[PDB]
Amino acid sequence: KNHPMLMNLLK
Amino acid sequence: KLSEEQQHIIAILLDAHHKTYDPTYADFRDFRPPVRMSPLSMLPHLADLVSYSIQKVIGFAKMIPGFRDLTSDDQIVLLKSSAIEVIMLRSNQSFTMDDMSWDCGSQDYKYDVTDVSKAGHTLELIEPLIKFQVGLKKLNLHEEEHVLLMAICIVSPDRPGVQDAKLVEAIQDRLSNTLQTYIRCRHPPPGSHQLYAKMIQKLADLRSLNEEHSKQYRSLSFQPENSMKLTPLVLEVFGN
Ligand SMILES: C=C1[C@H](O)CC(=C/C=C2\CCC[C@]3(C)[C@@H]([C@H](C)[C@H](CCO)CCCCCC)CC[C@@H]23)C[C@H]1O
Image (cartoon, rainbow over all chains, first blue to last red; front, side, top):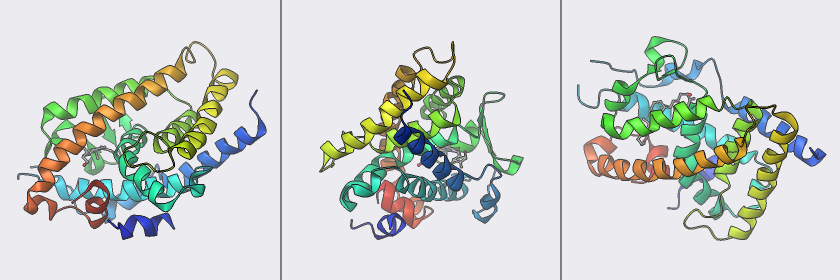
C-alpha cells in the first residue's frame, strides 16, 4: 500500500 | 473583497465538478444491477456506485488549486481519508427531502434507507447519514459553496498520516478565505447567516460519520465472502 490504482487515477 | 485569484479558484472548482458529476446519471447502467427483494441484495450495485463515486472524487480532487504541489504520499492520504466524506457531500445533490432518498433519475436508481440497509448497514447507523443530508440540504448552498466545501474537506491538514501538514493547511486556508469571502460578497441574507460556521460544522459531523463508516466497513470487509463482492478500488481506498 502501495495503492497503484489510486496513484494511477491521480496521474 | 472577492480577489481575482479567488474567482479563478471558484471557476476551477465549478468546472472540475461539472466534469465529474453527471446529473443525468447515465453511467449507472454499467453497475451490477440493483436487487430489491436476499441478504446483502443491494451490496454489488452500491459497491459499484461507491467505487464509481471514488473515481469521480479523485478527478475532482486533482483540479483543486494547489493539490498538485503536494507529495504523492500526501495526495493519497488526503483522498483515502476524505473519499467517503466527499461522497456523502456530493450525494446531497441527488438527495431529496420529499421522501429522504437519493433520487438518481429512475426508480431503479432511487435509494432509500431500506436499500442502504440491504448493503450491510443496520437502519440505526444509517439514520445519522440521513440527518446529515437533511441539514446540509437546508443550507441550500450555492453550487459555488458546494464545490468549495468538497475541496476544503479534501485538503484537511489533520488527517492522520499527513507529512507536509504545513502545506495542506496553506492550501486549505486559500480555499477557506475564498469561501468566507464568497459568502459575504455573494450570499444574501438571511441564508448567509453564519453560513460559514454551519458549513464548517458539517465537516465536523462528517468526521464522526467517517469514523462510524470505518468501523462498519471494518466489520463488513472482515467477512471475506462480502469483501469478495466489492471492487478493487474500494478495497484499495477503504482498506482490505
Ligand atoms: C453521484 C452520486 C449520486 O448523488 C448518488 C450517490 C448517492 C450516495 C449514497 C446513496 C446510497 C448509499 C451510499 C452510497 C452510502 C454507502 C452505502 C455507505 C457505505 C460505503 O461503504 C453507507 C455508509 C453509511 C453508514 C455511516 C454513517 C454513502 C453515500 C450513499 C453518490 C454520488 O456520488
